[PDB]
Amino acid sequence: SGFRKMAFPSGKVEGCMVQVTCGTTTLNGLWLDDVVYCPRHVICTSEDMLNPNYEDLLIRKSNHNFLVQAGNVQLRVIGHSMQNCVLKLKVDTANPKTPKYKFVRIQPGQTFSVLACYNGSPSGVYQCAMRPNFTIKGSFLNGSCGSVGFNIDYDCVSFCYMHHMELPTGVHAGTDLEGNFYGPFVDRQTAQAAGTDTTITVNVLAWLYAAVINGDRWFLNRFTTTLNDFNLVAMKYNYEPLTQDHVDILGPLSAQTGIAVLDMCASLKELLQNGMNGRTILGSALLEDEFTPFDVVRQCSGVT
Amino acid sequence: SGFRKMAFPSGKVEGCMVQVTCGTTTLNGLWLDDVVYCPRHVICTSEDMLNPNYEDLLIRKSNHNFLVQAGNVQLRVIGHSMQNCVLKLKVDTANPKTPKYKFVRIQPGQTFSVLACYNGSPSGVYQCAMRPNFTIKGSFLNGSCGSVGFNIDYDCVSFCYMHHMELPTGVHAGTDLEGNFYGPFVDRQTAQAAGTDTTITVNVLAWLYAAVINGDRWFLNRFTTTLNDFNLVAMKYNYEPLTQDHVDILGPLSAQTGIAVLDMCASLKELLQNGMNGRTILGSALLEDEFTPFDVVRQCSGVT
Ligand SMILES: NC(=O)C1CCN(C(=O)Nc2ccccc2)CC1
Ligand SMILES: NC(=O)C1CCN(C(=O)Nc2ccccc2)CC1
Image (cartoon, rainbow over all chains, first blue to last red; front, side, top):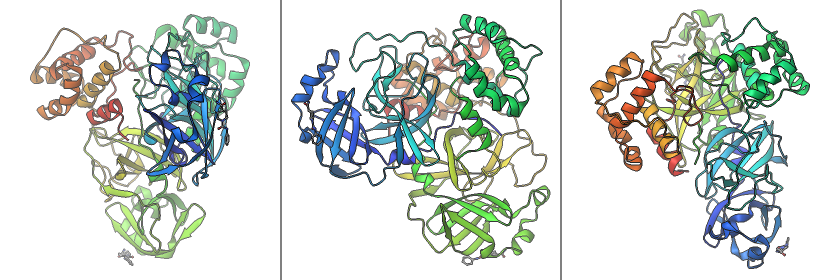
């Protein structure tokens, strides 16, 4: 029992963090096989960052201008390429701690663990969501760039995020491991405003199931609703619309708890319209939307 | 920028988790040097757990009745002793992944990362507090016992918690690594009620500093207070009393932000008396008390 915002174990990812230095800029790299991945903006001074021409900046850079350090041993760079907004640094040594891994471009609403790093050294691990506007609400100081987001399926690490930018609003943007930004974001220090930060409706409902399973039930009511009816209330509250897919995904939690999905929707409708009245659910005074249905099944079943 | 409930990297601790089986009971052990540490209640059936005589139960147990497994390799048990509420299983192999480590008995209000494990396999990592009533609010299913709480200082792991019990109320109790329960708890399945769960005042104030540093300032007011005055309001709200020590510990955050500690106390007094009025602080609708002053300095400076 109990429910907690839980990160994946960071061990397999700790073993892949290196320091990448180009001139005066140091940040984090991901060492997998004989490739170190980092944000291409390692080649920018902060001045460059106002209007960088990455192609022009890169021309001036040779393999020997990329200083790659793993703990207290230096890696030889035998190759470098720009893929989208990441650099791939070919080193002469395969990372001996390379776990099984994939690159996956996640969907908005999906959750992942972030290993916050400085100078290739991990400082902490926290669980995140990709917001519907493709921002994340991270904890990232100067030198945190190249910190990666991941999920783990038994022994395989799916890398889904590399950290690049803090937006002027203090939220975070970055790329998949192919270097493609999540959302409309660019590795340029400019006015980039994120859109509306909507709540991940399916996640909130997942977390209401987690509550019920863990004994927090006060918010169960005698009402049901329809998807159309529920989505009228969702709209008003900047909740993501709920689809039959979302309903389908909640099926197992529905089944286990014996509370139909539309009944819980009607529970959630009342919570939105009437607030918590000073009560909490799983120790929270607002509706948590950074647990997926998969997350709740995982934590309430005990998958390793 | 951004502030997050961040666990220590779990890598060094992942490398020390084993499976311990005695008859039909399997749970987690901590393999450090040539000793595996586990909850002594590995020797209880759930029936025993109603009124166990650990000395009598242990007599029936030989070294060969403790099955210790590290991934898919078995460890030979050459010795076993009962220290308080833990078993120490002497194996013939030193854990080759033993990090630098200490056992430390933490103080209430202190925070630590928990690596939730099942069958010696880590499922997730989350940050915790030792509550003032010496309970923790964990996420622990059947087979999670021997899951450990820790802090990391650069490369040294201070083990501070081993998980033993879920209380009838769904909170968690367990021991330091010397086998001494935190609080009045015993490894017996009985009515054990925890005392009042007071809020960790110094932690809340630390987290208000974190808010200010991260741009959340709406709750700063024009009032100050005294320790005595503040503690009258604390009492009423089941907040731990604030001492000159607590004030001293907040000194650096005070200094950095230029907000005196007693002014922030007066900010917190108003938050207690008037609530959040539907506003949030660092994405929370209640007062967070599971960041220590050290935690806020760490995360707002970027220590690895
Ligand atoms: N800006 C540019 O035109 C270039 C593009 C290609 N390039 C490489 O280093 N390619 C390479 C070399 C050795 C092994 C593997 C790959 C440097 C940058
Ligand atoms: N219940 C009891 O009287 C005993 C107490 C001592 N004991 C041991 O196994 N001691 C031991 C043996 C070999 C190497 C290291 C330590 C078993 C339990």
